[PDB]
Image 1 (cartoon, rainbow over the protein chains, first blue to last red):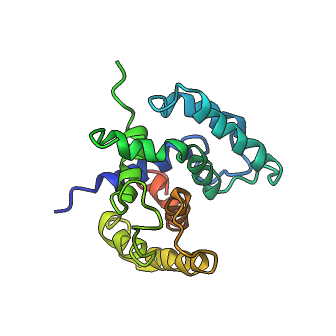
Image 2: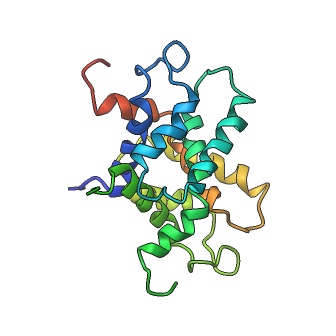
Length: 102
Length: 102
C-alpha cells in the first residue's frame, strides 16, 4: 500500500507535459516546433517565471539544440532542456520551502 | 488565482528530492556520495522500478559521471542523471495513463 510517491507521479506528469505534443510514437513524422518549448514553459511553469531571465535561459538552449538537430525528436531532448531553466533558480526553490535561513 | 501547476510543484518536489542531500550551499564541502543517487532511486522512484533494468540504467550513468567528476556537485548533475532512467520506460509511462491503444 504504496500511495504513488509525489516525485514519481511528478515524473509521470513531466512525461505527459511533453508527450501530449506527439502522437505516442511519432517523434519525426508528427512533432512540434522546438520553438514551442520556450512558449509552453510560459504557461505550464508560470509561477517561477516573471523576471523573464528564467525564460532567456530556455531560449539559449533552443538555439544550442537547433545547431545539432533535424527534428528527429529524442525523449532526452525535452528533459535536458528543462535542466537549463531549472538551475539559477534551483537553489532559490529549495530556499523558498525554508525561507527562514536565507 | 493560480493553484500552482502540478508540473511546477513537481519541479519544486524534484528540486527538494535532490537538495535535501546538501546543506543548502554546500555542493563540495558537504555532499552525498554519487553512489547514493542509484540507491535513493530505489526508495523515492520505486513504483516504475522492479524489472531492475531501469536501475541498471542509473548505475551506467554513475560510472560515466565518475570519469569526469571530483565531487564538485552541479545542480545539473542530478537532473541529467534522472533522464538516463526516464527514457526506455518514458514511452511506457505516457502509454500507461492511457492504456487504451497499446
